[PDB]
Image (cartoon, coloured by chain):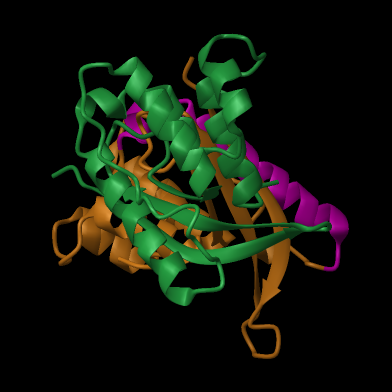
Chain colours: A orange, B green
Amino acid sequence: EEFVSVWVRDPRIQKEDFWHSYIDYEICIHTNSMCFTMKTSCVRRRYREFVWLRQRLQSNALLVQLPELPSKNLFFNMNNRQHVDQRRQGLEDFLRKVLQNALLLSDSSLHLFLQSHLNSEDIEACVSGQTKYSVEEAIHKFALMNRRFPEE
Amino acid sequence: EEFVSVWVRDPRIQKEDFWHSYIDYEICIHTNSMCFTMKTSCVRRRYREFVWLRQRLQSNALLVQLPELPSKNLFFNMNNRQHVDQRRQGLEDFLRKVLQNALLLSDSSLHLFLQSHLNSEDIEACVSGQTKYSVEEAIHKFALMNRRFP
């Protein structure tokens, strides 16, 4: 019987030796549902991308009540363990709830967010019909790159 | 439209401690079909397991002619680059033909052979209903273990 499971884990600093470092997380999906292209996926995303995601979803579903995100960057300090953990929990809760909703499950944005390398610009390009590649193509190409699959 | 692609590659010698040696191969599937559980898979199998597979398939589809397997087995010398290559080619051709056939595509044995770690004893157990886990379970657990998922 159909299930979908999601973990957010493994916080890591990025561009650490630059100005403009940021923290991102790993998002792992495991499902047996027809809804997803891949039954498993791990992808890395940061809070600002979750924000984009939330608002993208909100604007295609005016009547839907999106779940909360955890606290904003302004109130986030990576040296406070409790911060980084609260953020990860919150981002898990957010996705868990989102994924319980079939209308949202039907948004290619969410799928590309979860099962592709594409950033928000390209996601928007892709679901709006303006890229050479389809949504399925992008997802498959991510799995091949990501699983170091040989051949083609 | 739906596609399915298979490669057999990366022959390797397997040296269990003893005077025990064999070659196995990597079998990689890439598909976008609803027929398969996973859209990608890489698993390692050996010639003898193919032999098992072919007889198992033959016996659940008694009206289908199965493509042949490569036939030079006694002769075969795993230190002859060309022997091992001629094999892997044959095993690719075997699977490619097999997969073009929808009756065979609906045999769980094939799926477990391609998308799980289970060996033949367990495959048989599993498709017979004698294991605690289902077929879908075994395939999903393989992908999780294999993709180092938490």
Q: Is residue B26 left or right of residue A130?
A: right
Find out whether residue B147 is within the magenta segment.
no
Which of the two residues, B106 or B63, is positioned nearer the viewer here? B63
Task: Say if the magenta span includes residue A101.
Answer: yes
Rendered view: A84 above or below A38: below
**Image quarter of residue B54:** top left
Q: How many dots with numbers?
A: 0
| Residue A54, horizontal then vertical, whole percent | 44, 47
Q: Percent from the top left, x then y, of residue A114?
A: 46, 50
What range of the chain is rendered magenta? A79-106
In the image, is B76 to the left or to the right of B29?
right
The residue nearer to you, when weighing A1 against B86, is B86
| Residue depicted at 40% across the width and 49% down the height | A55
> Nearest the camera: A106 or B102?
B102
Q: Nearer the viewer, residue A69 or A39?
A: A39
Which corner quadrant of the image does residue B1 belong to?
top left
Residue name at image x 42 percent, y 54 percent? B28
In the picture, residue B32 is in which quadrant? top left
